[PDB]
C-alpha cells in the first residue's frame, strides 16, 4: 500500500545507511525497491514485519 523513502526509513529505524545496506546484502533486512534506476524505496509492511521479527527473537 505504502512505499517509504530513505529519510522516512531512517526516521523509523535508528540505523545508518551502511548498516542497512549490509543487512540487505546479508538477506537480513527488507530489500530496497528500485522504482527507477535513480529512485529507491521500501515496503512499509515489510519494514514493520522486520521490526516485529526483531522484537520476537
Image: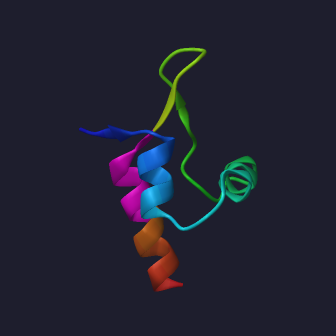
Q: How is the image coloured?
A: rainbow
Majority secondary structure in the magenta region:
helix
User: In which quadrant of the rendered image does the N terminus lie?
Assistant: top left
Q: Is residue 48 magenta?
A: yes
Query: Which image quadrant is residue 3 in?
Result: top left
Residue pictured at 47% horizontal, 21% vertical: 35
Q: Is residue 34 left or right of residue 56?
A: right
Q: Is residue 43 within the magenta segment?
A: yes
Q: Residue at x 46, y 83 (%)?
A: 56
**Position of 50 relative to 44 (above/below):** below
Q: Quadrant of the C terminus?
A: bottom right
Q: Nearer the viewer, residue 26 or 44?
A: 44
**Which segment did they paint magenta?**
42-49
- Most extreme residue toward the top is 37
45 to the left or right of 17: left
Q: Position of residue 46 (x, y in %)?
A: 41, 52
Q: Residue furthest left?
A: 1
- Count of labels shown? 0
The residue shown at (46%, 52%) is 9
Q: Nearer the viewer, residue 3 or 8?
A: 8
Rendering coords of residue 24 (x, y %): 67, 50
Residue 6 coordinates in the image, percent (x, y): 51, 43
Q: Position of residue 8 (x, y in %)?
A: 41, 49
Amino acid at each position: 500500500k505504502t512505499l517509504i523513502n530513505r529519510k522516512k526509513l531512517l526516521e523509523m529505524i535508528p540505523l545508518s545507511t551502511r548498516t542497512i545496506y549490509n543487512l540487505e546484502q546479508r538477506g537480513d533486512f527488507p530489500r530496497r525497491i528500485a522504482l527507477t534506476s535513480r529512485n529507491v524505496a521500501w515496503d512499509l509492511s515489510e519494514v514493520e514485519e522486520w521490526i516485529e521479527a526483531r522484537k520476537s527473537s
